Length: 438
Image (tube, rainbow, N blue to C red; front, side, top):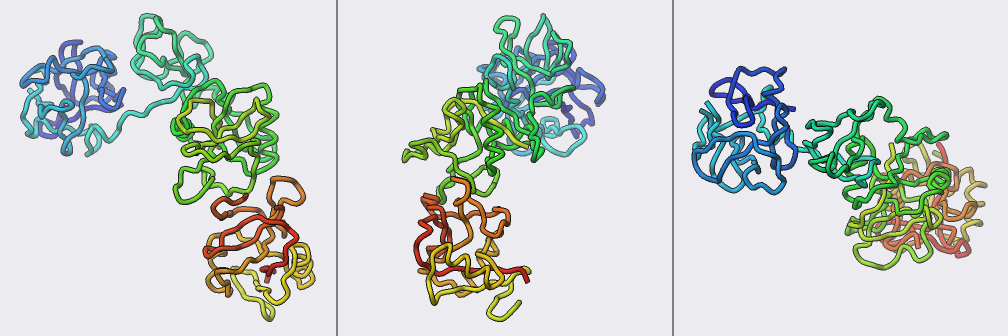
């Protein structure tokens, strides 16, 4: 993908033979000059599909093209200082001049930039391409791999007529036959994403894969997406009818990795919908990653994050205080239940307040006269549809700051010093907050 330039001589690096690596005039249309990181420490020649290496970790040896072995300590290179390149461990650098001789010199002949940039070669490092479908259960692409007595350094379409880019998850396909499609924009590609009718969002159900939660997140990110986030009923329902035939575990983007808070969506989505399995969430430590369970009726259960399963991706009048085009008012005299306090606001021209920003919650706790020991009703409720919390005024639920252990009770209140929320019985007399459009 990149050439290997040298400032002091204004030339690149030319791969001549499987045992001859020299320099030449910098040409970007020369296969013999292109290289690419196949691992975090291996540098492969695009021409010969062979990795650069040395015979020994000693001074003044020839740097030619070896066979890419993941365990070979003589192929591991890493960037020290800035543009200095040396074998992993030894202070023996990539000295130059016919063949490129490894040598303990660190002069300008041992400092190398990417042709076209002023950065070291490690600036465009290797990116693990987690495979899709295939028979490899979503393992990372392994370059270079042999197929039909030919080596490939990037995703190919040989052995096919459909143009689907695929790779070999092992160095030798014709022996192991382990492959998987590449997270790239295929000539088709749109078969992998099941588009939502209503919201027109795309989902990708990777059922026949075995990756950890962190790996599953990377595979969604590199595809320009993010792990699943269920914030609707129509979204949860559409996914249940889809994965109905499936029965294995499926990672989703619901985690509790944050040591400070509880459960949260990895894509910053507001926690407004619940669909837990009977017995979940359970009080185990480290079980901080939620997986969908289409076999057990598409419900959520938290397991250890290192488990290897499937995963799904996704692409003002008086007494009324003004803030952001709305007017607010706190009631503390006569404490009322959630339905009685609701009817009061709508006779006054407003509704139970709806918090859509952290700034709006901060305005209530800091300026509105909110005492730290108050317990005030808010319009949040799942009274109508179970487990699906909705606002009173019909405004969208875009911001949710729950309390530790909350939501543990079809009605929610503001309590604690931070002004966080908590669900409780709708039949308890309390104060309440109100909101009306100015």
